[PDB]
Image (cartoon, rainbow, N blue to C red):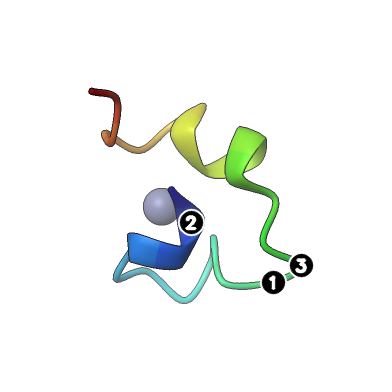
Amino acid sequence: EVRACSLPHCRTMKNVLNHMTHCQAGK
Ligand SMILES: [Zn+2]
C-alpha cells in the first residue's frame, strides 16, 4: 500500500495500484 510506503515517488495521489506495481506490500 502506498500509504505504508516510505518512498516520495509513490506518495502522490495515493495510487496504491501504482505503488504495489513496483513496491512490495501484498498479504
Ligand atoms: Zn512504494
Q: How many marks?
A: 3
Q: In this view, does 4 lie above or below 22?
A: below
Q: Residues within 10 Å of mark 3 (few under 14, many from 20)?
A: few
Q: What numbered label is drawn on residue 21? A: none
Give the residue type at disc 3.
Answer: Met
- Residue depicted at 59% across the width and 45% down the height: 16
Q: Is residue 16 left or right of residue 7?
A: right
- Residue depicted at 28% across the width and 36% down the height: 25
**Circle 1: element type:** loop
Q: Distance between the residues labelled 3 and 1?
A: 4 Å
Which mark sits nearer the N-terminus, 3 or 2? 2
Give the residue type at disc 1.
Answer: Thr
Residue 9: give x, y in percent of width and height: 54, 66
For ligand 1, tell me if the residue under mark 2 lies within 8 Å. Answer: yes
Asked if the residue under mark 1 is in contact with the one under mark 3, i.e. CB atoms within 8 Å, the reply is yes
Within the image, what quadrant is residue 10 found in? bottom right
| Residue nearer the viewer, 9 or 24 | 24
Marks 2, 1: nearer the viewer: 2
Q: What numbered label is drawn on residue 2? A: 2
Give the residue type at disc 2.
Answer: Val
Q: In this view, does 11 lie to the left or right of 1?
A: right
**Circle 3: element type:** loop
Which mark sits nearer the N-terminus, 2 or 1? 2
Residue under label 1: 12
Question: Quarter of the image containing the C terminus?
Answer: top left
Residue under label 3: 13
Q: In this view, does 26 lie above or below 14?
A: above
| Residue nearer the viewer, 8 or 25 | 25
- Residue depicted at 64% across the width and 34% down the height: 17
